[PDB]
Image: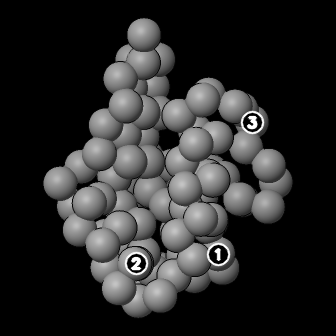
Amino acid sequence: QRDIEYSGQYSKDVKLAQKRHKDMNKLKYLMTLLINNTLPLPAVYKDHPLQGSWKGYRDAHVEPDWILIYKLTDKLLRFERTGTHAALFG
């Protein structure tokens, strides 16, 4: 069975998105698709593996400048970060 995980930073990121008036239902919907293993994700998410410092993780677009970084293996799904390109990659 796949474990569902949230990094410490992820909870902070979610709180910041809430504070900044982001549409939280969009993030919830995407998260639920991942938790349910409903794959592949719809094309609108532009889902892809990351390289560089985020090697081993994936990038999905909640919105054009609202990114979800997560890890998906046979053993785990981990929600790692969420926010802007500048915050997550800069």
Estimate the x, y position of residue 11 in percent, counting from the top left: 26, 60
Observer-nearest of 44 and 29:
29
Observer-nearest of 14 and 79:
14
Q: Give me the C-alpha separation between circle 1 and circle 2.
A: 12 Å
Q: Secondary structure at mark 2?
A: helix
- Answer whether labels 1 and 3 touch (C-beta < 8 Å): no
Name which of mark 1 and mark 2 comes first in the sequence.
Answer: 2
**Residue at the location (55% across, 56% down)?**
28
- 62 to the left or right of 76: right
Residue receiving disc 2: 17
Observer-nearest of 84 and 4:
4
The C terminus - image quarter: bottom left
Estimate the x, y position of residue 27 in percent, counting from the top left: 55, 61
Front disc: 3 or 2: 2
- 26 to the left or right of 71: right
Residue receiving disc 1: 63
Q: Give me the C-alpha separation between circle 1 and circle 3.
A: 18 Å
**Residue at the location (82% across, 54% down)?**
43
Which image quarter: residue 14? bottom left
Estimate the x, y position of residue 48 in percent, counting from the top left: 62, 51
**Residue at the location (57% across, 77% down)?**
23
**Residue at the location (37% across, 73% down)?**
88
Q: Give me the disc on residue 40.
A: 3
Q: Quick one: label 1, few (<14), some, or many (20+) residues within 10 Å?
A: some
Query: Given the image, on which type of amino acid does mark 2 rest?
Result: Ala
